[PDB]
Amino acid sequence: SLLSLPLVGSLPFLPRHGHMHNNFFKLQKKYGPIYSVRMGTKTTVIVGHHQLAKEVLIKKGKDFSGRPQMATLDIASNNRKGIAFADSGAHWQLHRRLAMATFALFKDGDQKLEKIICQEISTLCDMLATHNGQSIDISFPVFVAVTNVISLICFNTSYKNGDPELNVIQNYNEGIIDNLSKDSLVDLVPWLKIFPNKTLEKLKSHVKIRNDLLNKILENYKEKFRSDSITNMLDTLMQAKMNSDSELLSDNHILTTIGDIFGAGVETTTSVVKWTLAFLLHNPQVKKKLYEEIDQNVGFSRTPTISDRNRLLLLEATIREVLRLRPVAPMLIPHKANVDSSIGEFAVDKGTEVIINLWALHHNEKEWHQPDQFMPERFLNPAGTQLISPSVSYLPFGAGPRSCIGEILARQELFLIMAWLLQRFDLEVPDDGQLPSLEGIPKVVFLIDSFKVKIKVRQAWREAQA
Ligand code: HEM
Ligand SMILES: C[C@]12CC[C@H](O)CC1=C(C(N)=O)C[C@@H]1[C@@H]2CC[C@]2(C)C(c3cccnc3)=CC[C@@H]12
Image (cartoon, rainbow, N blue to C red):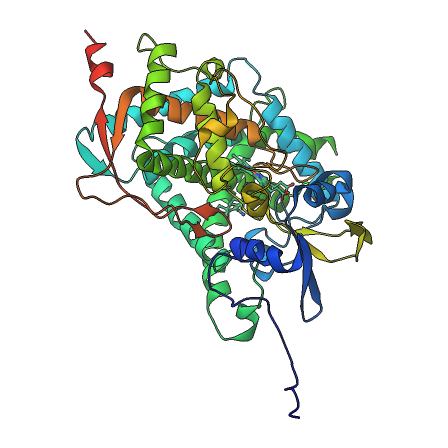
């Protein structure tokens, strides 16, 4: 005969316990593949089935192409300018098209995308070879390689070995990623609006070093820009300013688009490489089969080529399986409803935040055989002769208006970095028994805990030098 306590708030699970993308997933067993949460006035919908996800991303793509406003993303994007964190509208559509246009320039020519990548990988494999017999963290060497690539794609410039500017870029990259969000971008409770903290203070300072550095590059480039030479992204963006839309192509607009491209080009790829090495250290059977495949298909007469993706199918599968088990963005980047719409015939109102739980799509037990397993074989027919698409619930690069604009660069960097390393190096467990933790660290990107790997030059790659 006792009364029930008045309830002021309620959340499905504890905050800051487990990974958000996995807590939403576990929650589907209670409430289904689509449900909503209310935080004050803000409403958020989480979608964990491929059918509903393809509706949000593709079929109704234009309706759910907005980006919500976050205090941190404002600072990082210079008030919602750029591509990734910009709302759907004039700025985003223009710059995304220009950035996409830039990548199209890299069909075979004097700067074929493969040759830029290979030029930097040869330097990487040379540096790593000097550590023959030692255990090292490959974060920075790989960071340098991909930084020089995207730097060439953006400014036709690279960094000389040992340039301190690289160490400066790494510093503010780790600083922004750290403070851009505690754990995932999706944050149930707005902790930084509640308690006194220094998060935005710290974030602004790392953004100042980033903005100042890029502002130096841009100003210097106004002197080198010639309209008759459009070979990099900064040319494309400047070429567009003159033609005018000039209010959409100010210096601050160009700054952020380069920042978005510059940032995503180094951190996403560096992360996926580290993830792949981690899985290969936990699966020596796979790693052994990858050496055999590359020995019988590429050998040592030459270095790997992008065409070799026709031969090295277990490698393409491995990369596919990593992008599945540990997606770079397990919950994509939050979407926002631009207008009143629906998902699964449920109503969704304008301004409502919408998150696609890609982690749920890649771990759904009905669409995948033993989804929590690392099985690159699942992307190959039973004969290991050609690649397959075993499930329709697989969107490593997203889909629709907001899909990845650098997917091409990503797949090529990943395939070539892994191909060059496997040809030349034995990548074994360090002298201490430590294996990397495959748990992961959910940030704006799904990072892996730093770890060491014992690198040795392969006996076969050596004998082939006589
Ligand atoms: C393995 C590497 C990568 C993976 C798995 C990946 C995947 C993704 C995903 C899931 C999204 C969000 C999709 C959505 O919000 O619906 C995205 C967006 C984006 N990606 Fe990537 N990406 C990778 C690398 C790159 C690279 C190398 C670039 C180079 C420029 C890049 C640039 C972008 C940008 C700018 C966006 C936001 C576009 C927009 O908001 O319209 N990404 N990517
Ligand atoms: C966080 C980071 C990297 C660190 C840099 O100092 C600041 C930064 C970006 C920036 N505003 O300069 C763009 C972000 C990128 C991280 C990757 C991001 C979030 C990204 C992305 C995330 C996941 C998959 N594909 C692309 C789109 C925008 C990119």
